[PDB]
């Protein structure tokens, strides 16, 4: 459970830095 | 059971990159999250401009039986290898303006499966001799070689911290190795057939293997056991490629059902099909800044998603 | 009444139009179709497209309700229709010649690297040849302008002209297609029995559909023009001529494996 | 690399003259080339441009329809043919390499230059001053102005900073207003805001005084300033 | 237009790269790739030319691993050369069982469904002298033929050729190894070309 907790914690912290999770509005997306 | 599902994550082909004609076996993302490198049986290694779907560099090869390619973290060099047992290293940034091959690491006899850079002067290779090796590019000879496989080694990956690396072989086994000393840190088993795709989780505390038995697996480096299994009943074919995303929620897994599947790496049950190829999915990668996903398949087309 | 007849003529026209539109679309979409075969099939589909959008709906009223053409329209109608039909037949011959060179001397058919100029040269020579064979005679006709006349080229008054036209567009294509297919068979035949029977059957089907859909009208027209200068069989042969462009997009570019893949992607 | 040029000298007004350039020690046929000039007493001027594959060709409005540019890849040679020469055309010329792909450094090598003495909404840049006496051991700050904003749509900026020493050819100090070309001491800097930009030479030493120039490369024609003369 | 003065040159560069890739593919898409198994570290590639044709043969016998993770990269080959001997039918290591198992594995494999197979039998003189005092009864007790090379050789040839399970898609061109090998393989690949060629345009 400790090993799974370590990897899930890293997922939560970098949530807003993942475009593929939360797609950026086309104003900042260079691939449109 | 307390993790919310990401749900259906649809994606659209922003860019279709045409120009590769024969089969495609490898790809790697650059450091600036804008350049790409791809390897095919035309004897070609291409560096793509990703934003505008432009071509920056095209490199011919010597042994067209390639299986892998790498991108230097400083953007200066590239590397490749395959069925010819040697690893080639090319210099991108010369005043001459053309890419030249600077190093040719030799000393293997089984087919090379992969190669990844450590810095501008250190590399790691794994081949069919059942042996891995750390090479010092300036000297030209191995500084340490790693033995202990009974079957051919098909993959490896380098840690973000740049101190260790993990390999996997046709013995249904994987092995974690230190770099500067030579000891075998650990040996993992569990697959029902050979292992043909491995990846290194960005936090450096896990890794994922792909098999030719219709299953993907996550093991942990410290706990010395398998963490997760990723497979579906409608699937009967084999994995070919595995990669993660910045946070790690999306495990992008290639398949032979012709369809990349994005898996919710935490619930072990979701398949966001990125359908759109007509053949087997070979390779795939994700940018450093998460701005895209590229997949390449046997049909000679490379697709960008977000 | 005549409403049912008009509906069915329009139905045939729409079917032809769609049948060749799909070929054109599946050639412009996929970029792996850049061989000789796909270029030639595209030429075929374009030559068959304009029959369904111009000739049939314009011809419906001239015989169905009222002869509302005049010269300034009927000259255009005749020229368009004849050009399209002749071009379609000539594309059939060109595909079959590609097929014969395929299994007649295959050593020289494997190491040529000519890209566009040659292929488009052929694709344009087809249309130029079709025009210069058929078209320049419709316009030079003048006796066909008698008042109250159903509109159809003046040279119907000369059976020799019809004989020359039908010789340069019916005899030569059937001879060439039959020869190419027979040579294909011999060059393969010289387990085995089943394959030989399948090949013979398919080649016979192609040649037979060509002959059935294009013989009666030429024969019947020359028969009537010989001395007995219209019965229902005349309409039968007339429409049987147009009925080829219904099946020409079904034998050649639908059996093909590459084009089958191109379609099934969509 | 190496670039050696021929054709300079003294020419009468009118007529025509051709200046040739020979490249050595690099892949010639993957480069775009510019012909630039400098007045015998005043700043620099651009002339012409040819690109990779002998496609795009550009001339200055002053030289339009009378100068033509060309290249020859088997022998690694470049040509500027020059018709309608007038006494105002006296200058000394530079052949400048430039490779246009993502991330490259254009204007990174200039030839030794060849002398040639002859017997609108264009962005023209005004050099801010003409002489700044600064003693060795103290920083030097130079600026220049522009006629038009230079931030393009793709987030780029196009201002170039060059230095020339007596009896010498220019070298690339700054490219695209913020980047430092490799092969020069790392004590230079560049900055500024729209149409108003600045070069800085920190901790001035010997052999670091001379004429300084700026350039704009947002849209053709290419223009220059006057050139600040940093002296001892 | 939303480009600077130099993005045009970037686009031109990409266009040249695309042209070069297409030309190289056209150059490399009209060669006959034959794979040799058993006439002549890692892949040993051999190139030669015959009658306007470019033969790229792969001598791959230097690899010391299995074929499952290694053979599918040869999907597009024209043909396979297969070389075995006749003199070693009785040498217990025997060798006929190994050769037959190899041929059965190769011929009935999916990657070569439409791919024909050329098969060679060599070392025939040693076999002919052997059968003078060592008949096939040692290895073929069910054999009831005359003590001559011809009947036994035909027996062995039909024994290998009766292993074909794809009789209506690919043939086997058996030839006794004796420069007739090059002519045999040239005729074989010509016929493979014809049969695969009048197949992609219908014609069954
Ligand atoms: C529906 N169909 C359209 C084409 N059409 C003919 N078309 C050609 C063209 C050429 Cl080049 C040669 C022979 C023929 N047959 C003919 C013979 C007698 C009268 C008309 C024709 C008449 C009506």
Image (tube, grey):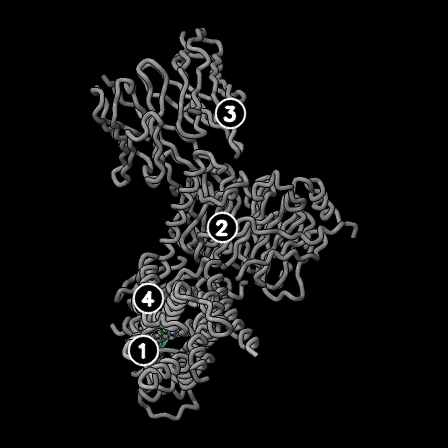
The Cα–Cα distance between marks 4 and 1, rounded to whole angstroms, is: 15 Å
SS type, badge 4: loop
> Whole-Å distance between the Cαs marked 2 and 4?
51 Å
- Residue B55: image location, x then y, percent: 45, 44
Labels 3 & 2 near each other (Cβ < 8 A):
no
Along the line of sight, the residue nearer the viewer: C226 or D121: C226
Q: Is residue C184 visible?
A: no
* Residue B233 can be seen in this image: yes
User: Chain under label 4?
Assistant: C
Looking at the image, residue D175 sits to the left or right of residue B255; the answer is left
Q: Identify the residue under disc 1.
A: C157
Q: Is mark 1 within 8 Å of ligand 1?
A: no
Q: Comparing marks 3 and 2, which lies closer to the viewer?
A: 3
Quadrant assignment, res C184: bottom left
| Pointer 2 residue | B17
At horizontal 39% and vertical 43% (from top left) the residue drawn is B101
């Amino acid at each position: 459970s400790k090993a799974a907790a370590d990897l899930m914690a890293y997922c939560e912290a970098h949530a807003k830095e993942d475009p593929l999770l939360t797609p950026v509005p086309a104003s900042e997306n260079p691939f449109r | 059971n307390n993790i919310d599902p990401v749900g259906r994550i649809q994606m659209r082909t922003r860019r279709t990159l045409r120009g590769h004609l024969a089969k495609i076996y490898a790809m790697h993302w650059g450091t600036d999250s804008r350049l790409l490198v791809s390897a095919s049986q035309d004897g070609k290694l291409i560096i793509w401009d990703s934003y505008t779907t432009n071509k920056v560099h095209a490199i011919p090869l010597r042994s067209s039986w390639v299986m892998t390619c790498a991108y230097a973290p400083s953007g200066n060099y590239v590397a490749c290898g395959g069925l010819d047992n040697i690893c080639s290293i090319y210099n991108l940034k010369t005043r001459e303006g053309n890419v030249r091959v600077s190093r040719e690491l030799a000393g293997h006899t089984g087919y090379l499966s992969c190669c990844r850079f450590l810095d501008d002067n250190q590399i790691v290779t794994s081949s069919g001799d059942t042996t891995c090796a750390l090479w010092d590019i300036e000297t030209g000879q191995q500084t340490t070689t790693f033995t202990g496989h009974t079957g051919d080694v098909m993959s490896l990956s380098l840690a973000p911290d740049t101190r260790l690396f993990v390999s996997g072989a046709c013995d249904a086994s994987a092995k974690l190795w230190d770099v500067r000393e030579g000891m075998c840190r650990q040996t993992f088993t569990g697959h029902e057939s050979d292992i043909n795709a491995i990846c290194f989780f960005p936090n450096g505390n896990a890794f994922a293997t792909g098999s030719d038995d219709a299953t993907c697996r996550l093991f942990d480096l410290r706990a010395d056991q398998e963490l997760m299994t990723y497979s579906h009943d409608n699937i009967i074919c084999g994995i070919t490629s595995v990669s993660f995303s910045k946070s790690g929620r999306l495990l992008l897994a290639g398949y032979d059902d012709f369809n990349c599947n994005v898996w919710d790496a935490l619930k072990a049950d979701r398949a966001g099909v990125l359908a759109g190829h007509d053949n087997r999915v070979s390779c795939l990668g994700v940018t450093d800044d998460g701005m895209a996903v590229a997949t390449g398949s046997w049909d000679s087309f490379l697709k960008i998603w977000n | 009444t005549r409403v049912t007849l008009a509906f069915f003529m329009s139905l045939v026209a729409f079917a032809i139009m769609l049948g060749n539109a799909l070929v054109i679309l599946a050639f412009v979409v996929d970029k792996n179709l850049r061989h000789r075969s796909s270029y030639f099939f595209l030429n075929l589909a374009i030559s068959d497209f304009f029959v369904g959008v111009i000739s049939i709906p314009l011809y419906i009223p001239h015989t169905l309700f009222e002869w509302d053409f005049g010269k300034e329209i009927c000259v255009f109608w005749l020229t368009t229709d004849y050009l399209l039909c002749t071009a379609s037949v000539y594309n059939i011959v060109l595909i079959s010649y590609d097929r014969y060179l395929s299994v007649s001397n295959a050593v020289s058919y494997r190491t040529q690297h000519t890209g566009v100029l040659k292929i488009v040269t052929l694709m344009v020579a087809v249309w130029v040849l079709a025009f210069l064979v058929n078209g320049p005679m419709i316009l030079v006709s003048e006796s066909w302008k008698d008042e109250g006349s159903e509109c159809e080229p003046g040279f119907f008054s000369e059976w020799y002209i019809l004989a020359i036209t039908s010789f340069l567009e019916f005899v030569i294509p059937v001879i060439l297609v039959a020869y190419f297919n027979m040579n294909i068979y011999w060059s393969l035949w010289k387990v085995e029995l089943l394959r030989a029977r399948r090949l013979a059957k398919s080649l016979a089907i192609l040649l037979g559909v060509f002959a059935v859909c294009w013989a009666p009208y030429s024969l019947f027209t020359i028969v009537l023009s010989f001395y007995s200068s219209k019965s229902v069989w005349y309409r039968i042969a007339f429409w049987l001529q147009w009925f080829n462009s219904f099946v020409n997009p079904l034998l050649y570019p639908l059996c093909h494996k590459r084009f089958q893949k191109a379609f099934l992607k969509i | 690399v190496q670039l050696v040029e021929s054709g300079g000298g003294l020419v009468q007004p009118g007529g025509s003259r051709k200046l040739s350039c020979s490249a050595s020690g690099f892949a010639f046929s993957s480069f775009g080339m510019h012909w630039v000039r400098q007045a015998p007493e005043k700043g620099l001027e651009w002339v012409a441009y040819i690109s990779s594959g002998s496609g795009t060709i550009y001339y200055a409005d002053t030289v339009k329809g009378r100068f033509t540019i060309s290249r020859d890849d088997p022998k690694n040679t470049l040509f500027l043919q020059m018709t309608s020469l007038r006494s105002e055309d006296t200058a000394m010329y530079y052949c400048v390499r430039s490779i246009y792909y993502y991330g490259s450094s254009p204007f990174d090598f200039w030839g030794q230059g060849t002398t040639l003495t002859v017997s609108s909404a264009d962005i023209v840049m005004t050099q801010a001053t003409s002489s700044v006496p600064v003693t060795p051991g103290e920083s030097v700050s130079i600026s220049c102005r522009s006629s038009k904003s230079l931030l393009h749509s793709n987030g780029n900026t196009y201002l170039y900073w060059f230095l020339q020493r007596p009896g010498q050819s220019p070298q690339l100090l700054i490219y695209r207003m913020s980047n430092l070309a490799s092969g020069v001491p790392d004590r230079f800097s560049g900055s500024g805001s729209g149409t108003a930009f600045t070069l800085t030479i920190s901790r001035l030493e010997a052999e670091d005084v001379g004429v300084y120039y700026c350039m704009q490369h947002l849209e053709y024609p290419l223009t220059f300033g006057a050139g600040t003369k940093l002296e001892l | 237009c939303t480009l600077s003065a130099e993005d045009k040159a970037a686009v031109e560069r990409s266009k040249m790269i695309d042209r070069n890739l297409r030309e190289d593919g056209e150059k490399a898409a009209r060669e006959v790739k034959l794979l040799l198994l058993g006439i002549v570290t890692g892949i040993v590639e051999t190139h030669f030319t015959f009658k306007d044709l470019h033969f790229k043969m792969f001598d791959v016998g230097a690899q010391r691993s299995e074929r499952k993770k290694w053979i599918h990269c040869f999907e597009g080959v024209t043909a396979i050369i297969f070389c075995v001997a006749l003199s070693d039918y009785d040498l217990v290591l025997n060798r006929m069982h190994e050769s037959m198992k190899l041929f059965d594995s190769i011929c009935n494999n999916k990657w070569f469904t439409d791919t024909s197979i050329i098969l060679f039998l060599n070392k025939k003189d040693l076999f002919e002298e052997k059968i003078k005092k060592s008949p096939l009864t040692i290895c073929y007790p069910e054999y009831a033929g005359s003590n001559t090379y011809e009947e036994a050789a035909a027996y062995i040839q039909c024994q290998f050729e009766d292993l074909n399970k794809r009789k209506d898609t690919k043939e086997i061109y058996t030839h006794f190894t004796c420069t007739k090998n090059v002519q045999f393989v040239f005729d074989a690949v010509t016929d493979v070309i014809i049969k695969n060629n009048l197949k992609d345009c219908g014609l069954f």
